[PDB]
Length: 194
Length: 194
Ligand SMILES: Cc1nsc(N2CCCNCC2)n1
Ligand SMILES: Cc1nsc(N2CCCNCC2)n1
Ligand SMILES: [Cl-]
Ligand SMILES: [Mg+2]
Ligand SMILES: [Mg+2]
Ligand SMILES: [Mg+2]
Ligand SMILES: [Mg+2]
Image (cartoon, rainbow over the protein chains, first blue to last red):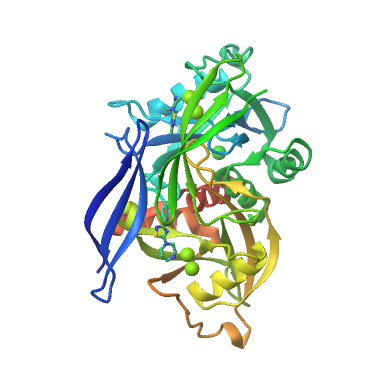
C-alpha cells in the first residue's frame, strides 16, 4: 500500500549520506522523510554483529563484548563485536574475521540471521546477527591475539551470560559507558526467558 | 584517553543533521568521523523509547506485542518494538506507556526502564530507553484495544508468543518482504539461547 516515490540527495560525505525521501502514505497522500544511508553498501547488509559465546569448562558461559570510543556518541560504548562486510565477503566470513580482529578469538558459526534493521525510522542500515561459539579450552583461544585495523582501538570485556543484564547495569553505574541497544535487548531477554 | 575536539555542522535537515567530528585517538593523533544526529533532542536523557510489551492473560502463553510499519528510510515494512521519540519534558516511562497505547491500543504497566542505550554508535549519537511494560490482557481496558495513531502513523499490531518468538519471526520473514528490527531479533535470539 505504501511505497517510495523518489529520493533526493541532500548531502553526501565519504561514509554517510542524507536524503529526502518522498513516499505515498496509505491514504494516497504524498509525504516526506529524512533518511540516512551509508555510502559503502554493495552486500546482503551493511554490517555484521557477532554474539560470541565463550565456552570454557568449569566456568560460566560468557558473552564477549567490546568497548570502544565512539565519536558519534562522544564517549565509550559497550557493544557486540562488529564491522562492515567487505564487498564480496559473506556475512559468516565477516563475522569470524571481525571477531578475530577485535577480540583475538577464533570461533565457530552457530546461526546467522537475515538482514535486520539498525534504526529504521532514521536509516536504511542493516546487519546480520551472527551467533558464534568460542571453544575457550582450545589452544588457539588460550592467549587471544586481537588484530585491530588502522584507527581501531578495542578493549575486550567478557561477561557471564547468566547475569548479563545485572553486570551491564553495573558497568553503566560505575564506568559512565553507554551499552548498545542490541546488547541490552539480548540481556533483557536472557532475564525475561521462561 | 579519547575525546572530542570539535563538531562541525555539514548539513541540517528538519529532523536529522550530519556533522564532521574531530577527535583524539589513543595514540595522541587527531582523526575525523562523520556523525549523524537528530535535531529534536533537547534535555531528554535520550532521543526515544522502545517498548518491550509483555501481554499477559490467564490461560494464555505470554506474547510480545510488536508493530509493523512502512519505514521510508528502509523503503519497506519493518517489524519492531513499539517506539517513539520522547516529547520535551516527558519521562521515558511516560513516553513508553503513551507510545504503546497510541500504537497498539494497549494500556501497559511499567516493569523496568533501561539506562539510555545506543542505536548505532558507529554512525549516530541516537539513544533510547528500552522500557519493559506488562499488559494485563484480562483487564477490560485491554480487551478490544483501539490504536490511536498520530498524523502519518499507520501501524499494524502483531502479537507473538514469547516461547516461540524467533521461529514465528522467521515465519513472517519467509512469507513477505519485511525486515525484522535488530533489537527484536536480538531479544528473540536470547529467548532461544536461554
Ligand atoms: C528522521 C525523520 N524524518 S521525518 C521524521 N518524522 C516523521 C514525521 C512524524 N514524526 C515522526 C518523525 N523523522
Ligand atoms: C561513519 C564513519 N565515519 S568515519 C568511519 N570509518 C569507517 C569504518 C571503520 N574505519 C574508520 C572510519 N565511519
Ligand atoms: Cl547459544
Ligand atoms: Mg567494529
Ligand atoms: Mg573491526
Ligand atoms: Mg513509533
Ligand atoms: Mg508513535
